[PDB]
Image (cartoon, rainbow over all chains, first blue to last red; front, side, top):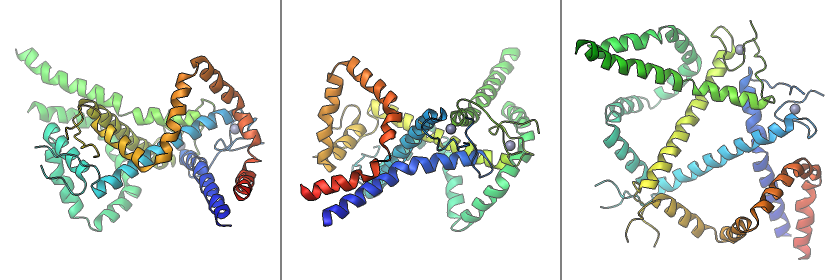
Length: 172
Length: 179
Ligand SMILES: [Zn+2]
Ligand SMILES: [Zn+2]
């Protein structure tokens, strides 16, 4: 009795995972428009779910595949985070006792700061911003969500004059 | 002296401008490419005129917010991809010291070796599928190409039995009961 239920649950969860790409590419295709789907060029079916006869269906499958690939990658990265959180990646820090946790992250950041040498200047600013934002981060996300495209639109006309006087500054 | 002295830094300025303007549009190119994948390789129109493509919304159009979002999202992925690439490069030089599971550090692909060894350790059944894959390589390459092409031909036929798929767990479950 138990094993039948276990197998049914496993199959249903596998179906959920396999249909995730449907939902995800449908969401992204919604992003293309003002939050609303469309109709595949050629019964007017959305290009996120075409019938097998529809030519776009072939494309859809390819699309479903790529999304799925990214998902796995994300999952992998997510997995790769947890191990790094738990300190199961015994990465030797640049010259020694091991970093109990986040060894990979600390090593990677140390290497980047040591080599690129401008992230050294960037890090103080980012640390300032994050530390000063226990809750300000939430508000600036809201501002970015609303004003961010707007401020980008206002800065963009002066976006190309920006390199000109940046060059002037570099000359001086 | 003065001529070349000025041109040098200014040459760097011009080259930087050109490279940044060529490489900062890649989010737009990839967004347009995916939107093309959505409709058999075509642009279509936005919801808002001149019928501009939805990946090049003017600021007046309401989609410029929307577009930016996905453009930004695409931009993020690029960094991630780049990061992967960067990692995929560093491991080759062995610049990632990862101690192997129980000792000298691996000369190259240390991170890849540790990850694969740990993953194989965690799942015993996974390795069971490894040999057949090699056999797939070990089989006739032409046979593998024919199989893949038939699957492409059988993809629509693959899901032509998609409706019977749902009962698959029950009947197999029934087998598990009778097993
Ligand atoms: Zn279609
Ligand atoms: Zn638009």
